[PDB]
Image (spheres, helix red, strand yellow):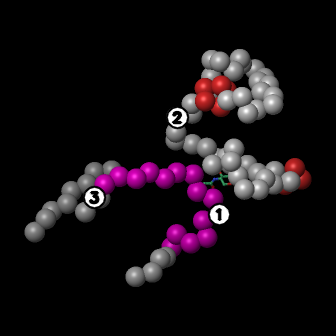
Amino acid sequence: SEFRVYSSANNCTFEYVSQPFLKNLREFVF
Amino acid sequence: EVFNATRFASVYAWNRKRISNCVADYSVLYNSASFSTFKCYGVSPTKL
Ligand SMILES: *[C@@H]1O[C@H](CO)[C@@H](O)[C@H](O)[C@H]1NC(C)=O
């Protein structure tokens, strides 16, 4: 309900936005 | 967002802004008459 682990980000170099990913089986390959 | 800023910083502490993942059309700023000087080193301003 709050934010975490991605705190104190000195500087950040990349951002991209897409449409959302997620009785339903969800397969991914990386 | 870079050329129009409410206040510019002093030269003792210049800003360094990162520009990435975009298409840069330099013809609008190059054609714009609002600039007093436009000096390019290395390559000519029209092939960029
Ligand atoms: C942040 O600044 C540092 C300078 O210490 C630089 O090495 C780094 O590439 C910059 N970007 C990120 C995402 O850390």
Mark earlier in primary sequence (1, 3): 1
Pointer 3 residue: A21
Tell me which amino acid carries mark 1. Asn
In the image, residue B45 lies in the stretch drawn in magenta = no
* Residue A24 sits in quarter: bottom left
Report which residue position mark 2 lands on: B23
Query: Which chain does the numbered disc 3 sit on?
Result: A
Q: Secondary structure at mark 2?
A: loop
Q: Which mark is residue A10?
A: 1
Depth check: A22 or B4 in front? B4
Residue B32 screen position, x and y as percent: 67, 29
Q: Chain of mark 1?
A: A
Determine if the C-beta at disc 1 is less than 8 A from ligand 1. Answer: yes
**Picture residue at 51% right of the left edge, 73% below the top:** A5
Mark 2 Cα-neighbour bin, 10 Å: few <14, some 14–19, many ≥20: few
Secondary structure found at label 3 = loop
Which portion, as a residue range, is magenta?
A5-19
Left or right: residue B43 versus residue A5 is right
Residue B48 x, y percent position in the rendering: 62, 22
Q: Residue at x 61, y 30 (%)?
A: B28
Quarter holding the N terminus of chain A is: bottom left
